[PDB]
Image (spheres, coloured by chain):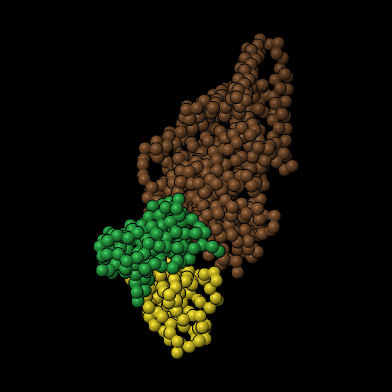
């Protein structure tokens, strides 16, 4: 009905720097839903980055994402934050913050109510 | 640990049934979802949990499974159907996405 | 994946268990028949006391095996991995809004993680006047994935696909259906669960759940893979609602603690409480089709679990507050239904005794054969001809209850268990005729009570007649009269003290 997700923080940064993207949700609480970050490189398909479930502490990262990225959520501000440090050349892409349900068994529900991404440029 | 969208390309006329097949290495306790993305816009979910259809999707997208293979079929190629179709296997601590499968026109 | 299980040598263990049961029954029959030849009305105290010491030894054995299990479960520690999902299935049939909202709040405030807790509520609605339950369910959560369906018929005559997808995909599900009793909603919930979860907890629409109950059930179920079902300690939310309420609470505490801990020491818990129970989804799915077509009890599900080859447990760290009937003859109807379910199953478990410990066979044999022997002894003692016999029979019954209450007080550590002595009067008047009527069946409940009262009064009158037939002016009756008067005054003083302490502990 009114569920939406708006993320910001994208921009141009020097390689090896730091960035902090933030997606704020409207119409629902992030504590009852999963929050995932999806990156789509220019000219390539979607790639998963990280996922977090607030009120439980369950955080997951990709193999090429682990060791440099951190994911967090804040219920008071109802906003999910993704911090990146020591960024490499292959990080310039569009980052999407999308909500979903719970995993349970073999029934998930899919990634519903996506949000328009923001551009990140890690170059000199 | 990896997935393969077999067609990776398609070019059919309107009103022609098309099928997109996705192969996953493991499907023990993971769900497969099919999304649609148009250029310049975020992807839109079509069919959840392999066969279930999402609310608002027209009754022309059919999802099925045959073990390690998952098929999405469009009975008729409506004008608002040419986009990029993505196959995603969702699971805890590991989420994988498909690639390619862009439906062109002819 | 799970299948029926059998021991390594089914024939040897079967033969051993049947031989043990037959030998026990024959031994009991021998002593009662031996008792009639060895002693007559001449030594009633010897005739009864021997039996009292028998019950007392059985009670001490049960208490020891319960205390050992309690100490073992308290000493043992195992941190929860929180990697197993739990689905709470609730049944609704025209429930009171306050009790239902309390149950929903308790289920929503469990300490278990949100991402590993699914909630399903199935209602016997399908009408407009049942929409309040769905509305209350919607307003209670209002935060997670809520899926509500009205439906136009149960599973046995599309809404089936919608129900299945809503249950297996969302977190909070509220499904109403055509009224088919409490079995239909449980079957629908279990069928819609599918393979989404691995642990399923069953709850009713009138229970209050503790925060750590689900965590404790998960912890005890994750300790061993052979466990298939588990239960918890069920308390009473209204211990002071009526006189029968406090007695019901005391009986619930004693039964649950002693019996279930003793059975868990041998992993042979006979019955798992409906309001508080957890089952393996993989085992539950296999017996689900068979259970529905049986010709929805909590003693039947436990019997199916036991017959599947797996063992059931019980932990006292999982607590819940249920309710008990407060209006008379309703507890009697509940007891009659419980007796029918117990008997129709004493018949089920007589088949697979070899699949568990010998304690299951011993308990079943003694529980089946004792009430009849007690009834026969009571009838023989009353139909003797001396007020001495009946007076000392009543005195010995009250003494047995007094030592039972004292042992319960020592075990619990609280002195409130001494008030359980009124259970003797409760059972000696209502429970035995209800059990007999239930056995014969397989207002209505007032007939067995009237029959029991009539036969008891006739026996007392016959004894009084035979006693006054002999002249009491003889010098062989003065001592008997003195002893009878002293025993009667002692009984009156004991009953007065019982009632006085009851009123003191209730009024304050």
**Nearest the eye: C150 or A99:** A99
How far from the left and from the top, in percent, is residue B27?
A: 39, 68
Q: Considering only vertical position in the picture, is C468 above or below B6?
A: above
Q: Going by the image, does C449 lie left or right of B92?
A: right
Q: Going by the image, does A60 lie left or right of C184?
A: left
Q: Is residue A122 visible?
A: yes
**Nearest the eye: C380 or B4:** B4
**Nearest the eye: C442 or C375:** C442
Total marks in image: 0
For the N terminus of chain C, the image quarter is bottom left
Dividing the picture into quarters, in which one does residue A19 lie?
bottom left
Dividing the picture into quarters, in which one does residue B21 lie?
bottom left
Q: Going by the image, does C471 lie left or right of C337?
A: right
How far from the left and from the top, in percent, is residue A118?
A: 39, 67
Q: Can residue B1 be seen in this view?
A: no
Q: Which chain does brown denote in the image? A: C
Q: Considering only vertical position in the picture, is C256 above or below B21?
A: above
How far from the left and from the top, in percent, is residue C360?
A: 47, 44
Q: Considering only vertical position in the picture, is C184 above or below A41?
A: above
- Of all residues, the one furthest to the right in this rendering is C443
Give the color of chain A as drawn.
green
Give the color of chain B as drawn.
yellow
Residue at image point 52% right, 25% down: C415
Residue at image point 57% right, 38% down: C236
For the C terminus of chain C, the image quarter is top right
How far from the left and from the top, in percent, is residue C417?
A: 53, 28
Residue at image point 69% right, 58% down: C127
Dividing the picture into quarters, in which one does residue C99 lie?
top right
Residue at image point 36% right, 37% down: C75
């Amino acid at each position: 009905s009114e569920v939406q997700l708006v993320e910001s923080g994208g921009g141009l940064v020097q390689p090896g720097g730091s960035l902090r993207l933030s997606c704020a949700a409207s119409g629902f609480n992030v504590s009852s839903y999963y929050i995932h970050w999806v990156r789509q490189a220019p000219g390539k398909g979607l790639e998963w980055v990280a996922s977090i479930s607030s009120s439980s502490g369950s955080t997951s990262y990709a193999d090429s994402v682990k060791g440099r990225f951190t994911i967090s959520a804040d219920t008071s501000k109802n906003t999910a934050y993704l911090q990146m440090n020591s960024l490499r050349a292959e990080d310039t892409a569009v980052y999407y913050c999308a909500r979903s349900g719970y995993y349970w068994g073999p029934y998930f529900g899919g990634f519903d109510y996506w949000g328009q991404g923001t551009l990140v440029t890690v170059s000199s | 640990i990896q997935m393969t969208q077999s067609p990776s390309s398609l070019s059919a006329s309107v009103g022609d049934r098309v099928t997109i097949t996705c192969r996953a290495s493991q499907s023990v306790s993971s769900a497969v979802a099919w999304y649609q993305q148009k250029p310049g816009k975020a992807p839109k979910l079509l069919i959840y949990s392999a066969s279930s259809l999402y609310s608002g999707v027209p009754s022309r997208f059919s999802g099925s499974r045959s073990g390690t293979d998952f098929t999405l079929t469009i009975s008729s190629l409506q004008p608002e159907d040419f986009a990029t179709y993505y196959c995603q296997q969702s699971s805890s601590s590991l989420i994988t996405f498909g690639q390619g499968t862009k439906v062109e026109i002819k | 994946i799970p299948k029926d299980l059998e021991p390594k040598h089914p024939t040897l263990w079967r033969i051993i268990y049947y031989s043990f049961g037959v030998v026990l029954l024959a031994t009991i029959t021998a002593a009662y028949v031996a008792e009639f030849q060895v002693l007559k009305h001449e030594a009633i105290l010897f005739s009864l006391g021997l039996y009292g010491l028998a019950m007392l030894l059985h009670l001490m054995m049960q208490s020891l095996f319960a205390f050992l299990e309690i100490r073992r479960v308290n000493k043992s520690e195992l941190p929860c991995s929180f990697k197993k999902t739990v689905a709470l299935t609730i049944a609704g049939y025209q429930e009171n809004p306050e009790y239902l909202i309390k149950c929903l709040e308790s289920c929503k405030y469990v300490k278990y993680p949100k991402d590993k807790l699914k909630i399903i509520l199935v209602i016997d609605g399908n009408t407009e006047d049942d929409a309040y339950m769905m509305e209350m369910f919607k307003d209670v959560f209002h935060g997670e994935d809520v899926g509500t369906y009205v439906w136009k018929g149960n599973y046995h005559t599309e809404g089936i696909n919608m129900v299945e997808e809503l249950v297996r995909n969302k977190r909070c599900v509220c499904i109403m259906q055509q009224w088919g009793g409490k079995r239909e909603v449980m079957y629908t919930a279990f069928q819609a669960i599918g393979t989404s979860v691995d642990y399923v907890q069953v709850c009713d629409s009138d229970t209050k759940l503790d925060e750590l109950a689900t965590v404790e059930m998960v912890k005890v179920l994750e300790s061993n893979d052979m466990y298939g079902a588990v239960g918890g300690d069920v308390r009473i939310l209204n211990p002071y609602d009526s006189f029968i309420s406090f007695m019901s609470s005391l009986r619930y505490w004693m039964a649950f603690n002693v019996e279930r801990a003793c059975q868990s020491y041998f992993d042979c818990v006979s019955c798992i409480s409906g309001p508080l129970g957890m089952y393996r989804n993989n085992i539950l799915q296999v017996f689900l089709e068979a259970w529905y077509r049986q010709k929805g009890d909590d003693r039947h599900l436990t019997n199916r679990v036991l017959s599947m080859g797996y063992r059931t447990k019980y932990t006292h760290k999982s607590r819940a507050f249920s309710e008990t009937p407060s209006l008379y003859l309703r507890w009697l109807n509940q007891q009659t239904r419980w007796t029918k379910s117990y008997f129709r199953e004493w018949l089920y478990n007589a088949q697979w005794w070899h699949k568990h410990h010998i304690w299951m066979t011993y308990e079943s044999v003694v529980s089946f054969i004792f009430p009849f022997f007690i009834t026969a002894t009571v009838i023989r003692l009353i139909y003797a001809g001396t007020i001495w016999n009946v007076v000392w029979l009543l005195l010995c019954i009250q003494i047995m209850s007094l030592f039972k209450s004292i042992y319960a007080c020592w075990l619990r550590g609280n002195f409130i268990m001494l008030l359980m002595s009124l259970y003797s009067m409760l059972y000696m008047t209502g429970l035995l005729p209800s059990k007999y009527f239930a056995l014969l069946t397989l207002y209505m409940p007032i007939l067995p009570l009237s029959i029991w009262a009539a036969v008891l009064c006739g026996g007392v009158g016959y004894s009084i007649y035979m006693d006054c037939q002999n002249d009491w002016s003889t010098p062989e009756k003065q001592k008997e009269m003195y002893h009878l008067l002293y025993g009667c005054v002692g009984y009156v003083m004991y009953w007065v003290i019982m009632a006085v302490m009851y009123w003191v502990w209730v009024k304050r």
